Image (spheres, helix red, strand yellow):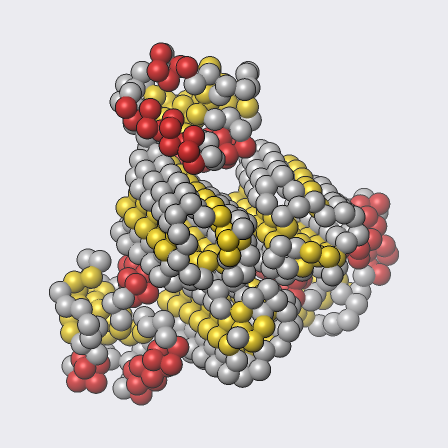
Length: 205
Length: 205
Length: 205
């Protein structure tokens, strides 16, 4: 489509809108947001999220959901998909993505991020600024790999998990679903579903 | 100006001189240094720092202060500014800097570094090799973000603070002025002025 | 040479083969491997490692040894060199390598990696995804700097040492030979030969 609607005009949204602008492929980039009006960082906020169900045509707008919170991103993305909107994979020109990587709709790969050979990312993943996902990783739906986090080869990350800024994993580690790993967490073993961990090595909080 | 004088021909200076050379915009790049003579890494050392006040014309030379120590960088930069020299912001071709970032004179952004949307860097900041400054950060004057350090969104770093190699911050953290955070420090709360911290999480030393 | 044989078709091998493909300089890229047959990631496995001594001509094939294990990489690389094969330094287009860096045969520098001014890398080094080696470092033979690890200026790393994913060093630190530093290790002092360390700060295990 000629236009992109970025849902969420917070800080993450600003970065995503600049990423899209850098691609040079959209005729117009706009925000939907429920808390701010006017324009943000030079992009217009054309309305609230009610426009998605009520106004925007999937024949005119692509959608990206720029919400950091994984549960909310999931809810909005699934609603957009259900309404028939395209959810482009947005990859910054300064990211490096392997030609053998597979990346699901609605995912965003930020400046300086790397996704290596054989990795599989499901829907709505964020690989944030300078984060790396090495070969043969599996990142399930709505996972957030925060800025500067580094996953070793063969790391699996379960659905909706958040891996904090500057965190890392040892090779062949498995993180379950709904896991929170704090900034700087050093994941050296498998982490069960629903756990919050932090530290070096990462331990339950 | 056609020429650049890099003050400081140590290791940091070598990297800064190569950064400038990569820009392909200067007719000549030279060093001022007080400890070495001849040439360093193929760039001539044309004299000591006494040339700044006594010899160099601001109509012919731009200045960059390639001194890692934040206090000394401050002293020399302020002296250069007072003598009317231009202090270009030097951004490596392989850095990514947001078009909405604001960066003060004399700052240096190294290869693979990223500065994201809405960030404000004051004078004489170093964002070193592969360091990232995410959206809406504020880095005050003569801050050094060391190689591979990653600041989350909305991180504030006070004047002259040094954030060590591989360190990181959680979102919305505030580091005061004159703070030293050691290599690998994981900054998970606000850090008062003048403190030295290290560890995961970062604690006072 | 017109052709490249990548020895090792595991995950590391897949990344190395894609790196070579990105260079656009080889007429053909193939694998030797002892555990897999057919093709891997779209590159043919033309035989086992017995082809090196018995079949491949050094007048037709360049060799790279895509084995993560430093001792095995050393053994195979030294054998290839002894049989007269060229062992190109392979640098990903998205890596940044200083024009004043020196890098020994058989070394590999991955996407987003940086090697800064005055650094010296001996034979068979791996600088993995987004790892950085700052100015004036010395990395001895068959060292592996894992993804996202960051070495400060003037870091020396002894022969065959493995520096884990997301690890970092303080400036002017010396790591001995045969050292293992775990993922996330924060190297703040010198590490004697043969030691295994981990933690923040890195301590013996």
